[PDB]
Length: 54
Length: 40
Length: 378
Image (cartoon, rainbow over all chains, first blue to last red; front, side, top):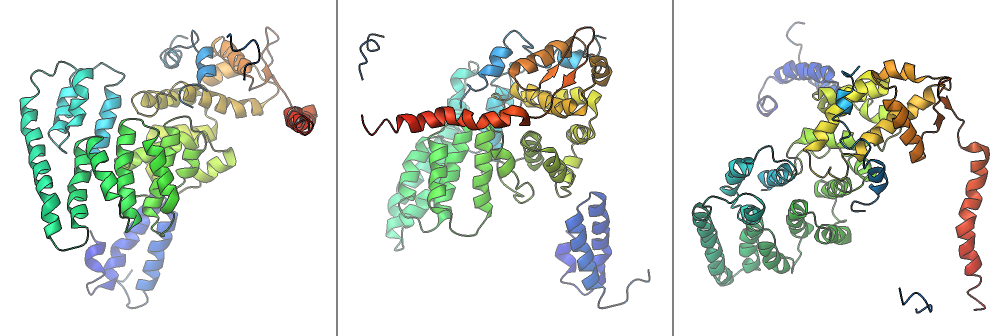
């Protein structure tokens, strides 16, 4: 329900603000390929803006 | 082909070896086996 | 369209063997008979179940609703030809006639499918009809219908890289083989664990994961076993929600012997009330027992059954006669012994049987060539 709302709006960082948490829970459930996918989305998201500080 | 004497005369079926082995041997397969460990 | 109906098939199996509840066949079977226009699911269960107190009238209203649907079909067959379009007769009755197949088992099927198969503008138009045979072929365990529709799917439905309903074919063949005597076909064709994601045979996707583990603990060698159900991280979640399944798995790789009978008891009691497992529930027991005993004999040559006894918990005379029956099966060669009592294993099949296999071919193989060299001169 988060992905249907964020990838059209303005905050590109608010996507990865929960997609990095999805990368946490797919490393937690050990979905290693989908963790790689979420990390790649995070790396291509962070190429625009500096982020909430840490 | 009348051979001069003989004219006078995998659904559930590969398992038959296991079943005829297991006719009067472990007829329940678990209901003693799950209860063996508290016998001794 | 088929999830509560495959659940009706689950109920067919669920009130096939046990009689511990003689009122599920009124509770969730009448709850099924009021939905889906399920007519035949009570019309054939009207004899094998109870007296059905007075179960005609609340079913008279629903067979009247079926009559309404059928009479607007019978008007629709000539109302759609007045619609100046292509095959609108075929469209307008194939819709509600696949729905007749949803209502009635074979009649709507036969009166529908031999008309709506007449033009095939897509392999979906074949394959939905094939699906509407596959539902009844799971309900009634046919062979002709639900292997010859798969032959038809293996006639022309190879084309089109649509992959969903081509993997459905793989899943149906896996279900059909594991529905009878499968070793390898369900493992090979349930390779596609993750990549299905939604079906009616996927009425519980996690039970499909139970299916693929309940065959991939048989058809799978130990390097392949760790590679699939350990080094499969994409399957690790849906085995991770299942404790005793994952327990039996990681113990069986861990060689945790005293919980094997516990976990096997869990899986066997699950095997009792799950369908397409009646040709399997006694075979599976000794199958997985001798499967664990494979590497248990690979363990040692110096081995006693007291070690086995405190490895299992009680096996002294139990496993004596049990492994005696496994030797009598021919597999699992070891010399179980009286008071000396040293379970001695052998060496693999090189010695002279590797020499012997060739002429064990060339006994009857060469009898073939002998007699078929005797074919020439009479």
